[PDB]
């Protein structure tokens, strides 16, 4: 579909048309708060008499579940300042740029990093630079170093004898993690192999004997790759303690309600490509729980077991 169609002929360079040499970039780190790394070009690209400059924001990731956020001012949003701004790729963040020879060329981000989460929306607006901001969350595990780029280029905006600047985001993801504690429900080529290697327990449709068992401790990250024919799941909005009596009219209890400061990722299961959810148990949380949820298939259910801080 149009959301992520690659243009194989597109090519640019870091400098674009600015005639600014790479040895003359203004390079700086992303602004990182907890696990959100932000490249904000709101006050970096305005026309000045010494423009164009190149403003290069460097995102360096070596730990799991980092959310990257890039803010690029909209064309026409302020008088004069952004008259000719442009962003590349237009289909960011589904499409990114990577280095090939001296050039930057388009690649599918999801093919680069298995399990990366792109939500359809950012604060109830479409996840696309036309709305001013894009976001994506990196997964619990990354196997190979990956470097990719975005462009937010105001250098063609000319005001009197002033020119805007060209903004670059370089995201450098180093490898981290090995496998995700949890389960992959597989159907039984490159994508099929990844699906088999990323979770500690694989569950095949035929002749499986062990239910999904997610064993978590303080600080740990868990995850599940849900079956393709999933109809619905109560993981993790309705966990049930299976060491207590089950009453179906009891109110629902989420993992978040049961485990203070736990975080669930892609809880709506609307991220593109990957039918996954990740969970993080805080290091603070020290109690023991034994819970289960369920996965209902499309026309038959799967039981899912979660243990937290088992003695
Ligand atoms: C670096 O970022 C902080 C925090 O930014 C906010 O939180 C991030 C996680 C991200 O979601 C950003 O979009 C947010 O703006 C900045 O601090 C804040 O500054 C703004 C504007 O002055 C203010 O409205 C907020 O109240 C401030 N505090 C918080 C907790 O957001 C900080 O200015 C940034 N520093 C630089 C040099 O850019
Ligand atoms: K009973």
Image (cartoon, rainbow, N blue to C red):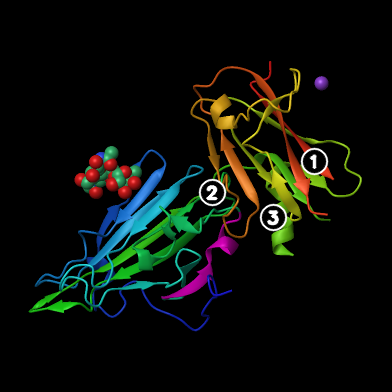
Quadrant for the C terminus, please. Answer: top right
Q: Which mark is residue 135?
A: none
Residue contact between numbered discs 1 and 3, judged by CB atoms under 8 Å: no
Marks 1 and 3, how far apart in space?
22 Å
- Can residue 219 be seen here? The reply is no
Give the residue at mark 3.
194
Q: Earlier in the sequence, mark 1 or mark 3?
A: 3
- Can residue 236 be seen here? The reply is yes
- Quadrant assignment, res 78: bottom left
Q: Nearer the viewer, residue 250 or 189?
A: 250
Residue lying at 28% horizontally and 68% vertically, measured from the top left: 74
Residue 238 located within the stretch drawn in magenta: no
CA neighbours of label 3 inside 10 A, class few (<14), some (14 to 19), many (20+): few
Marks 2 and 3, how far apart in space?
15 Å
Quadrant for the N terminus, please. Answer: bottom right
Secondary structure at numbered mark 3 = helix
Q: Nearer the viewer, residue 189 or 154?
A: 154
Give the residue at mark 1.
302
Secondary structure at numbered mark 1 = strand
Disc 2 versus disc 3: nearer the observer: 3
């Amino acid at each position: 579909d149009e959301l992520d169609k690659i243009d194989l002929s597109y090519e640019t360079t870091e400098s674009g048309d600015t005639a600014v040499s790479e040895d003359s970039y203004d390079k700086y780190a992303s602004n990182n708060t907890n696990k959100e790394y932000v490249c904000d070009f709101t006050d970096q690209l305005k026309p000045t008499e010494s423009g164009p400059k190149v403003k290069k924001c460097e995102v360096k990731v070596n730990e799991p579940l980092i959310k990257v956020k890039i803010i690029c001012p909209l064309k026409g949003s302020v008088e004069k300042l952004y008259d000719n701004i442009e962003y590349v790729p237009k289909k960011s963040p589904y499409v990114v740029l990577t280095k090939e020879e001296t050039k930057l060329k388009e690649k599918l981000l999801s093919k680069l990093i298995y399990g990366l989460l792109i939500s359809p929306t950012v604060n109830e607006k479409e996840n696309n630079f036309k709305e001013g901001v894009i976001e994506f969350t990196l997964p619990p595990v990354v196997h190979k170093a990956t470097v990719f780029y975005f462009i937010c280029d105001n250098s063609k905006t000319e005001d009197d004898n002033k020119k805007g600047n060209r903004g670059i985001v370089e995201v450098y993801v180093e490898p981290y993690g090995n496998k995700i504690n949890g389960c992959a429900f597989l159907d039984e080529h490159n994508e099929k192999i990844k699906m088999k290697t990323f979770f500690t327990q694989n569950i095949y449709k035929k002749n499986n004997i062990y239910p999904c068992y997610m064993k978590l401790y303080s600080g740990d990250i868990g995850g599940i790759l849900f079956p393709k024919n999933i109809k619905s799941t109560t993981c993790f909005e309705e966990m049930i303690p299976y060491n207590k009596e089950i009453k179906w009219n009891k109110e629902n209890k989420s993992l978040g309600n049961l485990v203070n400061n736990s975080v669930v990722y892609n809880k709506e299961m609307n991220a593109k490509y990957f039918n996954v959810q990740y969970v993080h148990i805080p290091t603070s949380y020290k109690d023991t729980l034994n819970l289960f949820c369920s996965i209902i298939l499309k026309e038959t259910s799967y039981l899912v077991y979660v243990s937290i801080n088992e003695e």
